[PDB]
Image (cartoon, coloured by chain):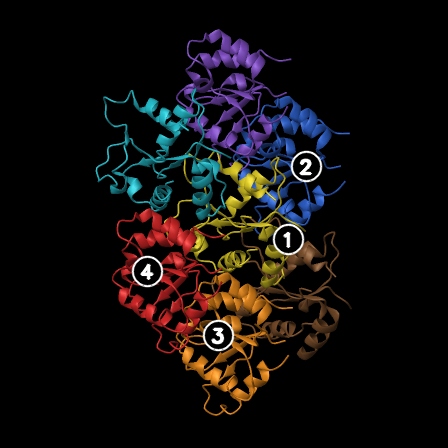
Chain colours: A orange, B red, C cyan, D yellow, E brown, F purple, G blue
Amino acid sequence: ERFDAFICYCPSDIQFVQEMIRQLEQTNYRLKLCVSDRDVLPGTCVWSIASELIEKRCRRMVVVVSDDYLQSKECDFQTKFALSLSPQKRLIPIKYKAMKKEFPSILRFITVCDYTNPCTKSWFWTRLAKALSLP
Amino acid sequence: ERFDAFICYCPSDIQFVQEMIRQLEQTNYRLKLCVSDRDVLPGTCVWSIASELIEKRCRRMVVVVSDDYLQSKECDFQTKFALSLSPQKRLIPIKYKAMKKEFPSILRFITVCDYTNPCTKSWFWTRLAKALSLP
Amino acid sequence: ERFDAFICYCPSDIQFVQEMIRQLEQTNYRLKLCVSDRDVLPGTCVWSIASELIEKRCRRMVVVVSDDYLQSKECDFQTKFALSLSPQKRLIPIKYKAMKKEFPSILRFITVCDYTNPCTKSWFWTRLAKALSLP
Amino acid sequence: ERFDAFICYCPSDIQFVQEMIRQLEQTNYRLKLCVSDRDVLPGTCVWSIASELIEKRCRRMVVVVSDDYLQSKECDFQTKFALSLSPQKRLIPIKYKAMKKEFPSILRFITVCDYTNPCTKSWFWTRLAKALSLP
Amino acid sequence: ERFDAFICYCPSDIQFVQEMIRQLEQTNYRLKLCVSDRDVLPGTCVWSIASELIEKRCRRMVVVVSDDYLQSKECDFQTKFALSLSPQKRLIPIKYKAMKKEFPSILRFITVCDYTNPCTKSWFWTRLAKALSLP
Amino acid sequence: ERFDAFICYCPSDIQFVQEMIRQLEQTNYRLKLCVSDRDVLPGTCVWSIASELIEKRCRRMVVVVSDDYLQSKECDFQTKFALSLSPQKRLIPIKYKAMKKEFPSILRFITVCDYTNPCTKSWFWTRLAKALSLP
Amino acid sequence: ERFDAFICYCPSDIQFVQEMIRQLEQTNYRLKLCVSDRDVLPGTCVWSIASELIEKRCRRMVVVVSDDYLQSKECDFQTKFALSLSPQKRLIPIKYKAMKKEFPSILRFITVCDYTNPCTKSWFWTRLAKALSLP
């Protein structure tokens, strides 16, 4: 029923989401993350997963930014529907890979949780799990 | 008499349907799937399998989308007759193979149950059997 | 509300439909023909004009067969939905022009009301108005 | 305050909107249409005109489809936000000009109110004003 | 002492500011606009006109966007200092000329008060004077 | 029976009258214009269309002035019969084309509704429909 | 009903009148100018626009002097009818273009509001709007 974070990801980047499940769910933190290919029954309509999941069930939204994120359209609509909801840091962008294109200009005024820097990798999962566990 | 899911498939893709029978009928789930080459006596008229089976006997319909699905016409009429029935997720599209053409534009607003992704194959049959077993 | 005949036509052949309105409605026969560009409000969904008009409101269906009829798809679905309804001569095909392609093979077992023959044109409108006015 | 129809249009097509104001507001129908360049004070935020105008103030939405409609992004987000609202024919697409590209595939299952056909122009404004005036 | 709107402009665009003084001050609206070359004594320090004028004296800020606006740095710092103040539509961007470069990406989520459109020029000054006169 | 405006035109200028029907009848104004080639049965006498139509049925008269208007005689007699009726602006002259002869000297003391000026074309149809709709 | 200034112009000079409407009506001055091709219904008599408009409705009269002004006769009669009314500066002549003929000798004892001088163009619209707004 309830969750803690909807996860918006391109389908070419599920190896990172499987890592996130291991680090945040199967660890001693006990967090619940709604993943689309795991908690959504087939046959649903697309306009209900924005009006029911992102609106009334999840509390935050994690945007897995990548290079193939800039080609899909459902991620664009879900990102803009999340930004349209503003009454608490309700949008967390994550960069994990070497991008060679431009960053999304919509997200330039939010602080990204970077992973590709080979000197700051000790603070990543602690900051992320402290962010998601906040009320 | 009654069923749980009509199955709409091209005749060049029955090796997958034979696998589906093994995974959903001969397993501990006990589901009943109406297959055309197994439960329809020869000599019937084509306009009765849409007015009697899909209307009053089956409860859902599973569309085995493929590359040779885009050439047959009975699958087109049965898909559109299923979409014309709307009073519950009464249409489940399944992709199982590497398609090289375009996806059907009629089905773009329903969530597909994908199988060709080599990282998500553990959730496939559980999601499908949880979807078909719903009232 | 009620009607007497739904009219299925390609949009490139409305000059004949305007003639049919003059010969069957504005004449001393007093028939009511549901035309799509005249009795359907914009904003409707396409899957309701087959489930409500052809099913429960009109009593027959007139198929204006032509050369550009073989390219549209909504006429194909409406023709096959009309043929799927069989409990009374509930489908009347009309040929009015010199076709250079093949006749539709779906309609070969129904008697066409031909118009292009320059010797039989006296019986056309009388036969058509006697057919449509039957209960 | 209240309205009857939000109007979604590309800024290169305001000559048609000025005609629509003359035919629907300054005529004997007395309809109120919220236009962006006429009723929105400058300095507003873009994410409030979807959460306040389209949600709680207007009752329907008129999409002026054109060739330059396929390049803007705010019309894409407003169209998809309108489609995401589904509890009454709450979306009316209008074609008024000779398009040379493809029609939008998102809107193929709603009936368009066509204007470029030189034989049906007598029914256009009557159908449109009967549609907008419905409760 | 008090004002109603600080005006941030490039020094190559004072002919428009002189027009704005005629249309908003010397007209029957009686508005007070703090202009830098008219109300600031020489010899002041630059870091006081942001901490005293924009903070505690003016109520809004009008950004005269142009092509030479993208080269100055004091306008960049004053724009970002205005955006950093967020407790009411406290920033009004104005476009008056044909720009050939890109719009500033910082201001894309605020509604611009456009002037170069040759069909909407009747609403410009009324909207602007209704915006500035609000409490 | 009743009308709003008799229309006096040379038979070489019916393409403009067909445009006038589209702009004033098939639009949201609902005006009725008596046209000779559309509402007069053949076999009538010419001296009754001036004693019955222009006298007791129509309320105004629209004179489509052109270059070939100066050759017909029935337009001369109908214009002079209209001028002989004076008890309200009961005669509206319309110029739509580049004339190379002289204007009619009989009509020099009435204000013409000009159309060939390429700067005033926005006011034409609004002025004409406001004139014809007056009691 | 009421106005502020009748405008007497040759029909070959309406591009300047369209500019005057933008500078005096659609600006923050809110003046009302009676233009003949915009506020006079067709079918009126010419001898009423001097006895009703210039006499009892407008308060001043603006004479757009030009080179083609010296060929029309209605401007001559309206100028002399305005001069015959003398009980307040009730006649304002405007020169805007390079004339190559002589100035009108009737108007030599009134001060012209010149526009073609490339050094005095800053005072033009302010003087004109201060003149027209006087009681």
Single out the residue that lies furthest toward the front: B1
Inspect this view and state whether residue D115 appears.
no
Chain letter for the residue marked with disc 4 in the picture: B
Residue at the disc numbered 4:
B35
Q: From the viewer's side, name the closer residue of A135 and B93.
A: B93
Residue found 47% across the figure and 48% down from its top: C45
Residue found 31% across the figure and 48% down from its top: B46
Residue at the disc numbered 2:
G5
Residue at the disc numbered 3:
A35
* Circles 1 and 4: CB atoms closer than 8 Å: no
Disc ID at residue D57: 1
Chain letter for the residue marked with disc 2 in the picture: G
- Secondary structure under the numbered disc 2 in the rendered image: strand
Q: From the viewer's side, name the closer residue of A112 and E93.
A: A112
* Circles 2 and 4: CB atoms closer than 8 Å: no
Q: What's the residue type where badge 3 is placed?
A: Val
